[PDB]
Image: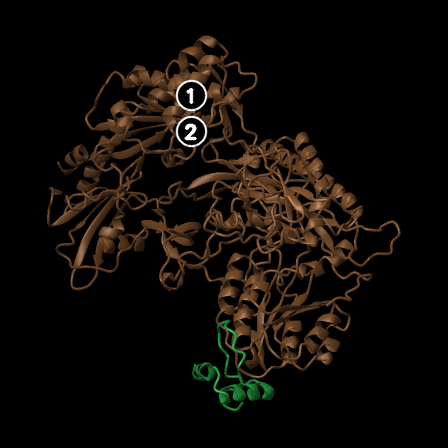
Chain colours: A brown, B green
Amino acid sequence: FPSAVTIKSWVDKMQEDLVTLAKTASGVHQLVDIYEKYQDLYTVEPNNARQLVEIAARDIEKLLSNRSKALVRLALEAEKVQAAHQWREDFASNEVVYYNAKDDLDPEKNDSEPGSQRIKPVFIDDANFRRQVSYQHAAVHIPTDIYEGSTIVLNELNWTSALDDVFKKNREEDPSLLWQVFGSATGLARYYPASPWVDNSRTPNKIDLYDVRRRPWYIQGAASPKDMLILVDVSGSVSGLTLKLIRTSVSEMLETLSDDDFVNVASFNSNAQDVSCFQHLVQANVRNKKVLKDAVNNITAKGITDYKKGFSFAFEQLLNYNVSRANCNKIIMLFTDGGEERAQEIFAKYNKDKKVRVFTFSVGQHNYDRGPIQWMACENKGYYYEIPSIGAIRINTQEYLDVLGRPMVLAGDKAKQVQWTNVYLDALELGLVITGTLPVFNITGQFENKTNLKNQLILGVMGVDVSLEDIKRLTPRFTLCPNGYYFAIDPNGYVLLHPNLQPKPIGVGIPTINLRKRRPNVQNPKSQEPVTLDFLDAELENDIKVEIRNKMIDGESGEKTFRTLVKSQDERYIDKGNRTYTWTPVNGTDYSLALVLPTYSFYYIKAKIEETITQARYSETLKPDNFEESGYTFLAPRDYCSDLKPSDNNTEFLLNFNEFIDRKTPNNPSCNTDLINRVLLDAGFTNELVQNYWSKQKNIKGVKARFVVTDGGITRVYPKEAGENWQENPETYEDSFYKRSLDNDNYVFTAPYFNKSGPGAYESGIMVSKAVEIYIQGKLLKPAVVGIKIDVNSWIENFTKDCKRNSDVMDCVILDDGGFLLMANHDDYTNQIGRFFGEIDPSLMRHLVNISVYAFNKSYDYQSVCEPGAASKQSCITEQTQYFFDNDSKSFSGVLDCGNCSRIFHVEKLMNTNLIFIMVESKGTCPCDTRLLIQAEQTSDGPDPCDMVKQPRYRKGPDVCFDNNVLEDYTDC
Amino acid sequence: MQLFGGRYDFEDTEVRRSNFDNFPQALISVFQVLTGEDWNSVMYNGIM
């Protein structure tokens, strides 16, 4: 076995070959030179990380204030118009003309139902709604199992006909409004602009199970947060059908709880106890609700009924105040069938002052006594509901809100405040939207003040949607680096804006579906959960990021510069970079906006090519017929100008960009001149690099291709024949290698993929990148990244010439920081290249992790798609893993033992690159095996939820909430 | 009423009116079994 000095010499030779090749044949220093030789075509403007956050916060506050003024008008008009309704009862001659959505739109239907008349719309196509839209009237959606022509809905269709004027006026004022919707307390929804519903009743093969009274925005605008305590009766009498109904009823009741409500499901049968591993009130988010649902479905009925112990348990759990609670609406929902004890003494001793409402549900069909349950409901400011079938479950477990809104309507104009909801997916297929809600009160004699009979309930809830694209256009991110961004969080932890929040719904637990018990065409329903991705689950958690989080939740300004390890775009690597967070509150609403700007990103290049000659000349260097002179050229599909639309068929986009710069000169008084000037400038620079330097040496020893990516969007590969082997995204802000090589200060080797269907191994070659670093006025700048694609075979040759090929005494392999194979010495390893080293040689990799040359950081990706097990895809959590160098040492030697044998190894890290070379005794000599140590997404289930409520994260609930009014009635049950 | 009283704790939703829950219903079910009408449906419920 060689000594340390000869191994170090081998490594020095290899590194002096690799660095010299990837430095000369790429053009780092040449581009650095030409980026300063001109130094007049552009200027260096600072990035004041404080002012950007304040400007973006003011613009977001202005947008939300506009969307609030668009709401108060609708509220005023709705109250005024319904105040003067006449309550007709015969619509045979005074028909209601309206456009019922989700109906067959053939021009031959002629429905003519008994009482009303449909409208046929024109339905032009539009943008800002990737669908067909008619701005002339307002559509209407009525739940499928509600008659469209009953008297209770024919009036809500007649008096809401005066909203369309305010809809039209709101949109005429701010032309950029999305859906405006009025969802009334009778299911009837009325939105504008009209659009055919995404799901007709039976025109597709699926049905439409939608109901406005269960949406997040409605439930949040119709009542203040609550502390619910579901209380199941699991005694022997509830066995059979009524228990099957109680399970579904609890599971549909939990579905009406936002993230600001707290819930716990106790049970009682001669002995009261909790039903899961929670023991107190939890926060009723996605995972907690999921655990409670999965724990309810396991209960069985046996024993004697005792209401006193159950109600003692409930009132005790509602008197904790050690845990974090919403602490607004203490209520309890008793799910039973009927007994003989009304338990007057417990109510007398626990809530003698009527502080905790008691809603009582009598489920199933039976011949028991529903007297005491009705009495409990009537006495404790509650209500009594009867659920005799699966049909009556949706409309009964959602009506208790009409009782929690009494102390809100009895408050007046102090209860009308806009209230934005969580991030969810629009029902009309518009992506991720937030909705602002504002209730609407019933006033039918506010003058005479004598009604107060139906005037204890609200009419409905108004709403206007704000898409998360309108917000991402107020935080423009095309003057930062690929590593700086904006992000804004709730006063609940959850994120509202992040480069890591995606349109898929967040998952909970491993998915499991049973095909053997699924009819073919029955339309098993879907979900209505919001996309609630916490802040500390979209990044890697430090002990400093928790400080920043809990510090900007409660509306504080400030900044902090620290040293955190960031994760790469492709979740395979992990960097170690400096960052400077700089947060602030959005003064109007309750959001906090921050901005992650790395060092080296406090200055940017502003293009100043005012001469039209240079602009034109540079613009002549992007036509597809000129590639043979300047190499294959791409272009980031940004919003350069409101005419040309991003295509993703990048050659077509380049054609359209060329043909648009052709017609109108770059003066562009109605167009984004900054991005276009920057793109022309960097195109000129890259073309000067290709012409002056790359074009001298047409081919080199092993360089399969040399690429240049830059900000602005231009990315050029020299050999056009090689351009067809460039799988990377054309936008230079999602190129993983770009960001990585920006963070590091040395040539970054990017391992290829393994066994992915696409030619990368011997058709593209190993990848190498390095960031251009210039100094204009003593200030750092990283405006471009240049690279190389080394060919694998010539590298094998250069590598071998006692590491002889296909040897049987030792193996000599090369990895990068991340543990991926790049150059082997057996021709059985180096045919599977780019594969995880610990997946072929497990024991040695495990020892390398053990002696602390590598280090990992497991995480969770709460938005993934997996294939379910039996116990096309489903939402799932996938545990990830990423390895990286931690120690700064250069050489690690030693010996690993695994029984009856021992192997020797020596590893050495190359200088100014992220490669490691390890030489070890072959596996053919030592029979060894521990386990495949795989680095890949694993469909996971954790973390354990009921070992996390014991120590929850910080949270600032809503300080304003309405309950316990004195002039209430509660004479109903 | 002793044997099948309250033992129709079936988890499904089919209605079984001829059960033995209380005394009048037991009398009705016994009369129905006596007159020999549909008595083979009151036996399968008692079996399952």
SS class of the residue under badge 1?
Answer: helix
Q: Residue at x 51, y 64 (%)?
A: A293
User: Can residue A973 be seen here?
Assistant: yes
- Would residue A174 appear left or right of A790 to someone viewing this image? right
Relative image position of residue A954 (x, y in whole percent): 59, 55
Q: Residue at x 28, y 44 (%)?
A: A820
Relative image position of residue A967 (x, y in whole percent): 82, 61
The residue indicated by pointer 2 is A647
Relative image position of residue A582 (x, y in whole percent): 57, 39
Q: Residue at x 71, y 67 (%)?
A: A382
Identify the amino acid type marked 2: Ser
| Label of residue A302 in the image | none
- Nearest the viewer among A64 and A4 is A64
Residues at marks 1 and 2 touching, judged by CB atoms closer than 8 Å: yes
Please tell me whether residue A826 is drawn above or below residue A721 in the rendered image: below
Identify the amino acid type marked 1: Asn
Q: Residue at x 58, y 50 (%)?
A: A550
- Disc 1 and disc 2: Cα gap in Å? 9 Å
Relative image position of residue A404 (x, y in whole percent): 70, 60
Q: Quadrant of the C terminus of chain A?
A: bottom right
Locate residue A57: give its quadrant: top right
- Residue under mark 1: which chain is it in? A
- Nearest the viewer among A506 and A144 is A144
SS class of the residue under badge 2?
Answer: loop
The residue indicated by pointer 1 is A656
- Nearest the viewer among A398 and A618 is A398
Q: Are marks 1 and 2 on the same chain?
A: yes
Locate residue A613: give its quadrant: top left
